[PDB]
Image 1 (tube, rainbow, N blue to C red):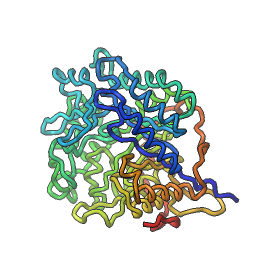
Image 2 (cartoon, rainbow, N blue to C red):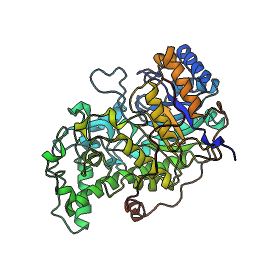
Image 3 (cartoon, rainbow, N blue to C red):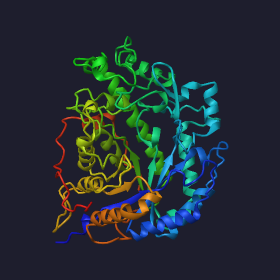
Length: 488
């Protein structure tokens, strides 16, 4: 047979500051020159955050797409594909961050009288990076619900970016579903004192979510159940808490119920927003995608505390990522993950980290459910070893010289475009990496054509999503090293 299906697309994330904090595009010459280097390297496309805080920052439904239209023109001009992130979250916000784009001010002004629009921890601190899913359907924003704001925003995107959708330049719409665009709770915020590898905190104490839990608990026959109060704080370790210790509460009926409620609220948050995104982009030659955070710390202990507080109900015998993958199937949505470049030996022992096992579990879960799985690197790397790790995860069993690979990533996106990537040995090493991802076949402008987006299949009962959690299956086999390594 033939081995064309070993080809893995490579995308490059554009710089964080590509559009200025005042929603102006001022880097036309630089970007054009940078994209020229990417085409010379055989890159398939680029990816960009489309910041809600810029486009709708001046007022409700006051959409200004003018800066992004200019960037998209340069990408189209370059013959590159484009993945657009609907970025409903804050950019920056930490002391020292250069690019700071909070969510629109008129949205946050509602918090002056209703601070419960923000994800809230047990101590009462409000996180302003992203609106709590508890107000998904609360009409608090000049009459609109949060989901309405997101759907209207994506609708205006489709109408205004018609030229690039019709031409096929845009191939993916990534729907931001939480902090950093990731479908998770803000369980480890730097802005509130979290330091790696703290277990994080459950962030479900805003009045809307607490009322939701109260109702669910009452209906379950346990009105005495309250939200956890024994889980510790951001920087604790699992054994210093009653919730996560051995024979802790997370193993009790009470704990199991809360964790199920917590993680299920997140899954249905994505399910409903993907449903509305599917209707907005119906007929467009795009695939919808979500982004899953790579919470690799405390993976090597039974409590998986850091994953649990982020909203991923993942245990040694419970696959908290295949449930998410099962939810995505009806939307034909792709699952975008991270940590593609990480090796277990690169992490510290005290963090109980296992990024390789995490990546293998997530990829395997997506592949078991027939999804397109794509990945990013979590940290900026320019060394051959990082690329060889990505190559391993891109084709776990290497090249199939007489057919399609057993499994493969649908794509990889490199974080992140910069001048240091495009100079000297960094650029030469990157170009070799693209060649190996393409299986030495060369850049293919027409690979993986995107079919017109079809309507989501019928919504599943939560039982069908939860069925995927157990029995937890072993991951598909991954080779230790790629068969197509890059020379240092």
